[PDB]
Image: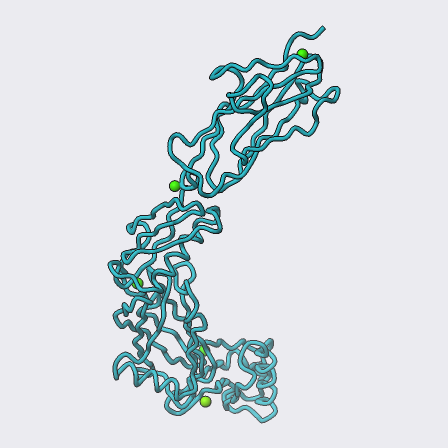
Length: 409
Ligand SMILES: [Ca+2]
Ligand SMILES: [Ca+2]
Ligand SMILES: [Ca+2]
Ligand SMILES: [Ca+2]
Ligand SMILES: [Mg+2]
C-alpha cells in the first residue's frame, strides 16, 4: 500500500503588488495519481488546522479527490490568488510565509515543519516597484523654469502617450520646472526628471525652400509649395507681410487673385522635418505682366513656433516665364508641295497650317495660333503673347514646304 505523501511543487517567493491581483499555482502529484486534499495555512495551530490569514489570501483546487487528478504529466493544480488591499503596509515586514500541505487517498499528508516544509513567501511591494516609466519625447517650452498650463498639459500628454502600460488610474502632476510626479493607485510614486521632459525652445522654424525660384508661366495657373519645420514639431503662424517691402508684394499677389493656403496651421505636430508644414500659393500670372528682367515677384516669409520664436525673414521668388519656354512644336508629318517657294498661295498656306495643327494636338495649347508666312515658315503664337512679352515659336520652311518646280533637262 501507499505510505508516501504527495509531492508539492510551488514558487518559494511570490512578489505581490499593493492594489493589484496576484495569482500562482501549486502543482501536486502522487504515485497513486490521486490527491484528496491540498491545504494552505499559517504555521501556528494543531496539525489538523487549516486556519489562514489575512482574509484576502485565497486558494482553490478545482479537481480534488478524483482518480487520475495528480499525475506527472497532468498535476493537480491549486490556485493561490487574491487582491492586495490598496492600503496594505509595504515595510520589510509586510510579507507572509504560508505552508502548503497535500494528502493522498491513503491518508498520507506531507509533514509540517516550521521554516522547512513546503512553503511560499508572499512579499507585498508598492506599485512603483512594478512599473518603470518611459521617457516622453521632449516638450520645447518658452521658459523651462516656469511652465505654463498648456506646457504642463502637453508634458502630461507626452508622458501618458509614452507609457500606455502604466495603470490607467495613475495620476500625473508637473512641477513649475517640468518635473513629473506619477502617483500610482496605491499612493506610491515615481518621478521623471525635468531634464527628461522639457527644454527651452532656442531654435526658430526653418524655411526649407529659402532662396527658391518658382516658375509661373504667363496665362497658366500654377502652384508653389513652401515647406517649413520646427525643432518642436509645431508652427503656429506663417507670415508674408513682415515689412513693407515684403508686405507690398504679398498684397500685389493677392490682388492678382492668388491664394495662400496652409491647411494644417492649427494642427498639433504640424511641422516636422519628415512631415513639414506646407503652404501652397495658387494663382495665374496674367499676360499683362511681361516676362523679363523685372518679371519676378520677390517675397519674404517668417514662421513662428508655439513658444513665440519667429524665424529670420527668408526669401523666395515667383519668376514669370513665357509659354514658349514650356512648349516645343512638333513638325508636320509631311511637307506641303508649293509651286513657287518665294510666295505661297492661299491653298498652300491653308494646307501647311492643317498639317502643323494636326501634328500638335495634345502637345501645344488648344488655343495656340499659327501664321503661315509668305515663305511657308510658320509662326506659332501662344495665348500669352503680348507686345511687351512675345511668346512665340518659328517652324522653318524646310520643315513645312517642298518645292515642286521641275528640274532642267
Ligand atoms: Ca501516495
Ligand atoms: Ca518605479
Ligand atoms: Ca522652435
Ligand atoms: Ca518654344
Ligand atoms: Mg479674384
